Image (cartoon, rainbow, N blue to C red):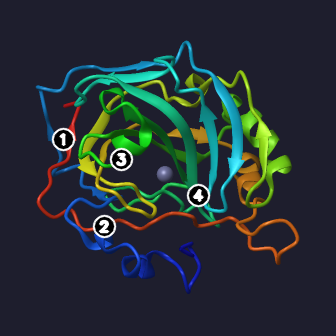
């Protein structure tokens, strides 16, 4: 498989190797704020990251993953629309070539500079590989980024990127606290969807926070210095690694807030 985000291997081609690309619950989507309905039955969302154990950072040629030890319930997501316990496995980002694009979800068609995905799996399925085969297998916590003030809790991430410039490179990345990437509010929209990259599995409950985090222009600039290619190949800057919004179809987006 040779999918990516260029003119020749990008989102509009993915459906050929991954036919679920055109399925019934694909992500990302546009969140119409005037159609999404406050759902008083959602419980409060619970983000328990106090015991999180980050291990490593990886450039996989599509994005970078900060990886976590998920061999126990150390960092978990519960509540909101979720039944049971979802364990944090990794986080990553999608971003643009300019500040006016980069996010995958959009809010009333507005694109943010980037989007953070904190990826969790449902413990009830025992491992991640099994969970991605289940309609309620994953829970991804989506956070928009906008350019403004710098986010201090992002800077360690920013600073390790020199060392994972190219595809395949990894660095040790211990004692990173993902709580520093959260906004103040946990108000959210939620809907059933998919992974936003191949294999585009329809296994995700999306929880997208309403309040974006601010990062600096200098911070986001350093994301754009990364490379899609591997070491000693011609340089393709890692930019615009985002899938555009997909048809909503027979789905409702529910809001946690009035
Ligand atoms: Zn993502």
User: To which residue does mark 4 refer?
Assistant: 95
Q: Are marks 4 and 3 in contact (CB under 8 Å)?
A: no
Tell me what residue is drawn at x 15 percent, y 51 percent. Answer: 35
Mark 4, residues whose alpha carbon is within 10 Å: few (<14), some, or many (≥20)? Answer: many
Q: CA distance from mark 1 to mark 2?
A: 17 Å
Q: CA distance from mark 2 to mark 3?
A: 20 Å
Q: Are marks 2 and 3 in contact (CB under 8 Å)?
A: no
Q: In this rendered view, identify the residue nearer to me: 81 or 222.
A: 81
Mark 4 or 2 closer to N-term? Answer: 4
Q: Are marks 4 and 2 in contact (CB under 8 Å)?
A: no
Mark 1 or 2 closer to N-term? Answer: 2
Q: CA distance from mark 3 to mark 1?
A: 23 Å
Mark 4 or 3 closer to N-term? Answer: 4
Q: CA distance from mark 4 to mark 1?
A: 25 Å
User: To which residue does mark 1 refer?
Assistant: 254
Q: Position of residue 7 (x, y in %)?
A: 56, 85
């Amino acid at each position: 498989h040779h999918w990516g985000y260029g003119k020749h291997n990008g989102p509009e081609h993915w459906h050929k190797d991954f036919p679920i690309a055109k399925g019934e619950r694909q992500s990302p989507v546009d969140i119409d704020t005037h159609t999404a309905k406050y759902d008083p039955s959602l419980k409060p969302l619970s983000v328990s990251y106090d015991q999180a154990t980050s291990l490593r950072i990886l450039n996989n040629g599509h994005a970078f993953n900060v990886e976590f030890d998920d061999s126990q319930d150390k960092a978990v997501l519960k509540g909101g629309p979720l039944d049971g316990t979802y364990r944090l496995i990794q986080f990553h980002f999608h971003w643009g070539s300019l500040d006016g694009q980069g996010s995958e979800h959009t809010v009333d068609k507005k694109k943010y500079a980037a989007e953070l995905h904190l990826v969790h799996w449902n413990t009830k399925y025992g491992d991640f590989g099994k969970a991605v085969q289940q309609p309620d297998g994953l829970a991804v916590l989506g956070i928009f980024l906008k350019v403004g003030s710098a986010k201090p809790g992002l800077q360690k991430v920013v600073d390790v990127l020199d060392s994972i410039k190219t595809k395949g490179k990894s660095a040790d990345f211990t004692n990173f606290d993902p709580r520093g990437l959260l906004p103040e509010s946990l108000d959210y929209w939620t809907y059933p969807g998919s992974l936003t990259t191949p294999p585009l599995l329809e296994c995700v409950t999306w929880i997208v926070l309403k309040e974006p985090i601010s990062v600096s222009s200098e911070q986001v600039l350093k994301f754009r210095k990364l490379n899609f290619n591997g070491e000693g190949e011609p340089e393709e800057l890692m930019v615009d690694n985002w899938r555009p919004a997909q048809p909503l179809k027979n789905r409702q987006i529910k809001a946690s807030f009035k």
